Figure: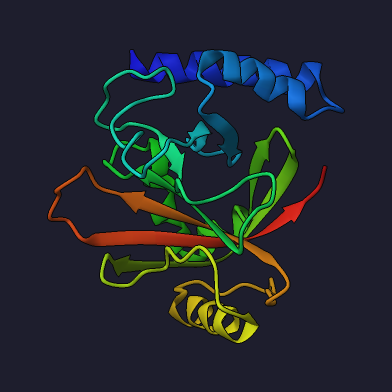
Length: 211
Protein backbone atom coordinates (compact mmCIF):
# COMPACT_ATOMS: atom_id res chain seq x y z
CA UNK A 1 0.00 0.00 0.00
CA UNK A 2 2.78 2.43 -0.98
CA UNK A 3 0.31 4.36 -3.18
CA UNK A 4 -2.37 4.58 -0.52
CA UNK A 5 0.32 5.74 1.88
CA UNK A 6 1.31 8.57 -0.41
CA UNK A 7 -2.38 9.39 -0.84
CA UNK A 8 -2.73 9.52 2.90
CA UNK A 9 0.31 11.83 3.12
CA UNK A 10 -0.82 14.03 0.24
CA UNK A 11 -4.19 14.41 1.90
CA UNK A 12 -2.61 15.42 5.20
CA UNK A 13 -0.49 18.03 3.44
CA UNK A 14 -3.50 19.50 1.60
CA UNK A 15 -5.19 19.98 4.98
CA UNK A 16 -2.03 21.61 6.34
CA UNK A 17 -1.87 24.08 3.45
CA UNK A 18 -5.54 24.96 3.96
CA UNK A 19 -5.18 25.23 7.71
CA UNK A 20 -2.05 27.36 7.69
CA UNK A 21 -2.96 29.02 4.41
CA UNK A 22 -1.16 32.33 5.03
CA UNK A 23 1.75 30.46 6.65
CA UNK A 24 4.78 28.38 5.66
CA UNK A 25 6.55 26.88 8.70
CA UNK A 26 3.67 24.96 10.47
CA UNK A 27 3.13 22.62 7.52
CA UNK A 28 6.71 21.37 7.60
CA UNK A 29 6.91 21.44 11.38
CA UNK A 30 4.15 18.86 11.06
CA UNK A 31 5.96 16.95 8.30
CA UNK A 32 9.17 16.93 10.32
CA UNK A 33 7.46 15.00 13.10
CA UNK A 34 7.07 12.31 10.43
CA UNK A 35 10.71 12.37 9.35
CA UNK A 36 12.94 15.31 10.16
CA UNK A 37 14.54 14.68 6.73
CA UNK A 38 11.53 15.99 4.78
CA UNK A 39 12.81 19.38 3.57
CA UNK A 40 10.00 20.23 1.19
CA UNK A 41 7.10 19.35 -1.06
CA UNK A 42 6.76 19.29 -4.85
CA UNK A 43 3.48 19.32 -6.75
CA UNK A 44 2.16 19.67 -10.31
CA UNK A 45 -1.63 19.85 -10.38
CA UNK A 46 -3.26 17.41 -12.76
CA UNK A 47 -0.33 15.00 -12.52
CA UNK A 48 0.87 12.21 -10.23
CA UNK A 49 3.71 14.51 -9.10
CA UNK A 50 2.66 15.36 -5.53
CA UNK A 51 5.17 14.08 -2.96
CA UNK A 52 7.48 15.20 -0.14
CA UNK A 53 11.14 15.98 -0.88
CA UNK A 54 13.67 14.46 1.54
CA UNK A 55 17.37 15.02 2.01
CA UNK A 56 19.95 12.84 3.72
CA UNK A 57 23.70 13.12 4.36
CA UNK A 58 24.41 11.50 0.97
CA UNK A 59 22.83 11.07 -2.44
CA UNK A 60 21.94 7.48 -1.62
CA UNK A 61 20.28 7.89 1.78
CA UNK A 62 16.84 8.00 0.15
CA UNK A 63 17.31 6.30 -3.22
CA UNK A 64 15.52 3.24 -1.88
CA UNK A 65 13.70 4.53 1.22
CA UNK A 66 10.39 6.39 1.43
CA UNK A 67 9.45 9.33 3.67
CA UNK A 68 8.87 7.08 6.66
CA UNK A 69 12.22 5.28 6.32
CA UNK A 70 10.64 2.20 4.72
CA UNK A 71 12.60 0.05 2.24
CA UNK A 72 11.24 0.77 -1.23
CA UNK A 73 12.52 0.34 -4.75
CA UNK A 74 10.95 3.60 -5.81
CA UNK A 75 12.37 5.27 -2.71
CA UNK A 76 11.65 9.00 -2.50
CA UNK A 77 11.96 12.27 -4.38
CA UNK A 78 15.15 13.61 -2.78
CA UNK A 79 17.29 16.76 -2.83
CA UNK A 80 21.01 16.50 -3.57
CA UNK A 81 22.79 16.26 -0.21
CA UNK A 82 24.98 19.20 -1.32
CA UNK A 83 22.12 21.69 -1.66
CA UNK A 84 21.19 24.17 1.05
CA UNK A 85 17.61 25.40 1.55
CA UNK A 86 17.83 28.47 3.79
CA UNK A 87 20.20 30.03 1.27
CA UNK A 88 19.44 28.24 -2.01
CA UNK A 89 22.44 27.65 -4.29
CA UNK A 90 22.64 28.49 -8.01
CA UNK A 91 21.20 25.16 -9.02
CA UNK A 92 19.36 22.85 -6.64
CA UNK A 93 18.93 19.22 -7.74
CA UNK A 94 16.36 16.73 -6.57
CA UNK A 95 16.09 13.19 -7.94
CA UNK A 96 13.42 10.54 -8.34
CA UNK A 97 12.69 7.18 -9.95
CA UNK A 98 11.16 6.69 -13.40
CA UNK A 99 9.83 3.13 -13.27
CA UNK A 100 6.97 3.55 -15.72
CA UNK A 101 3.81 3.48 -13.61
CA UNK A 102 3.03 7.20 -13.52
CA UNK A 103 4.57 7.70 -10.10
CA UNK A 104 7.47 9.72 -8.70
CA UNK A 105 9.32 11.26 -11.63
CA UNK A 106 7.50 9.51 -14.45
CA UNK A 107 5.97 12.90 -15.26
CA UNK A 108 9.37 14.28 -16.34
CA UNK A 109 9.12 12.31 -19.55
CA UNK A 110 5.94 14.25 -20.41
CA UNK A 111 7.80 17.55 -20.32
CA UNK A 112 9.52 16.26 -23.47
CA UNK A 113 6.41 17.02 -25.52
CA UNK A 114 5.78 20.69 -26.29
CA UNK A 115 2.04 20.35 -25.64
CA UNK A 116 2.40 18.99 -22.12
CA UNK A 117 4.82 21.80 -21.36
CA UNK A 118 2.27 24.45 -22.47
CA UNK A 119 -0.34 23.14 -20.02
CA UNK A 120 2.06 22.50 -17.13
CA UNK A 121 4.42 25.47 -17.27
CA UNK A 122 4.74 25.91 -13.48
CA UNK A 123 5.49 23.38 -10.75
CA UNK A 124 4.80 24.11 -7.10
CA UNK A 125 7.57 23.77 -4.52
CA UNK A 126 7.39 24.62 -0.80
CA UNK A 127 9.53 24.35 2.33
CA UNK A 128 9.85 25.88 5.82
CA UNK A 129 11.24 29.08 4.24
CA UNK A 130 8.45 29.92 1.81
CA UNK A 131 6.37 28.93 -1.21
CA UNK A 132 7.90 28.83 -4.69
CA UNK A 133 7.03 28.48 -8.34
CA UNK A 134 9.20 26.36 -10.59
CA UNK A 135 8.85 27.76 -14.11
CA UNK A 136 10.08 25.05 -16.45
CA UNK A 137 12.18 26.32 -19.35
CA UNK A 138 14.05 23.17 -20.40
CA UNK A 139 13.48 19.40 -20.62
CA UNK A 140 15.79 16.94 -22.34
CA UNK A 141 17.06 13.36 -22.38
CA UNK A 142 20.72 12.89 -21.53
CA UNK A 143 23.14 10.53 -19.79
CA UNK A 144 25.31 10.29 -16.67
CA UNK A 145 28.35 11.39 -18.72
CA UNK A 146 26.99 14.97 -18.79
CA UNK A 147 26.83 16.63 -15.38
CA UNK A 148 23.83 18.96 -15.31
CA UNK A 149 24.18 18.22 -11.63
CA UNK A 150 26.55 21.11 -10.95
CA UNK A 151 25.67 22.96 -7.72
CA UNK A 152 27.63 26.20 -8.02
CA UNK A 153 29.73 28.09 -10.51
CA UNK A 154 33.08 29.91 -10.39
CA UNK A 155 31.40 33.03 -11.75
CA UNK A 156 28.59 34.41 -13.88
CA UNK A 157 30.52 33.64 -17.06
CA UNK A 158 30.66 30.03 -15.82
CA UNK A 159 26.99 30.06 -14.76
CA UNK A 160 26.02 31.87 -17.97
CA UNK A 161 27.64 29.05 -19.94
CA UNK A 162 25.71 26.42 -17.97
CA UNK A 163 22.43 28.28 -18.49
CA UNK A 164 23.26 28.60 -22.19
CA UNK A 165 23.83 24.89 -22.72
CA UNK A 166 20.79 24.11 -20.60
CA UNK A 167 18.61 25.96 -23.08
CA UNK A 168 20.47 24.66 -26.11
CA UNK A 169 19.82 21.06 -25.05
CA UNK A 170 16.15 21.75 -24.27
CA UNK A 171 13.77 19.74 -26.43
CA UNK A 172 10.94 22.18 -25.64
CA UNK A 173 10.85 25.94 -26.18
CA UNK A 174 9.64 28.47 -23.62
CA UNK A 175 9.11 32.23 -23.41
CA UNK A 176 10.56 32.16 -19.88
CA UNK A 177 13.91 33.93 -19.75
CA UNK A 178 16.60 33.10 -17.24
CA UNK A 179 19.63 35.20 -16.33
CA UNK A 180 22.77 34.65 -14.25
CA UNK A 181 20.98 36.50 -11.46
CA UNK A 182 18.14 33.98 -11.26
CA UNK A 183 18.09 30.76 -9.23
CA UNK A 184 17.51 27.38 -10.89
CA UNK A 185 16.11 23.98 -9.95
CA UNK A 186 16.79 20.89 -12.02
CA UNK A 187 14.61 17.81 -11.70
CA UNK A 188 16.34 14.54 -12.63
CA UNK A 189 15.31 10.88 -12.86
CA UNK A 190 17.59 8.40 -11.10
CA UNK A 191 18.49 4.71 -11.07
CA UNK A 192 19.27 2.34 -8.19
CA UNK A 193 22.91 2.11 -7.21
CA UNK A 194 25.08 0.12 -9.61
CA UNK A 195 22.43 0.28 -12.33
CA UNK A 196 23.85 0.23 -15.82
CA UNK A 197 21.08 2.44 -17.15
CA UNK A 198 22.97 5.67 -17.69
CA UNK A 199 20.21 7.40 -19.68
CA UNK A 200 18.44 10.18 -17.77
CA UNK A 201 15.73 12.80 -18.24
CA UNK A 202 16.19 16.33 -16.93
CA UNK A 203 13.82 19.26 -16.47
CA UNK A 204 15.21 22.64 -15.42
CA UNK A 205 13.09 25.44 -13.97
CA UNK A 206 13.56 29.03 -12.82
CA UNK A 207 12.89 29.25 -9.07
CA UNK A 208 10.62 32.15 -8.11
CA UNK A 209 9.52 32.89 -4.55
CA UNK A 210 5.84 33.76 -4.21
CA UNK A 211 5.57 33.61 -0.42
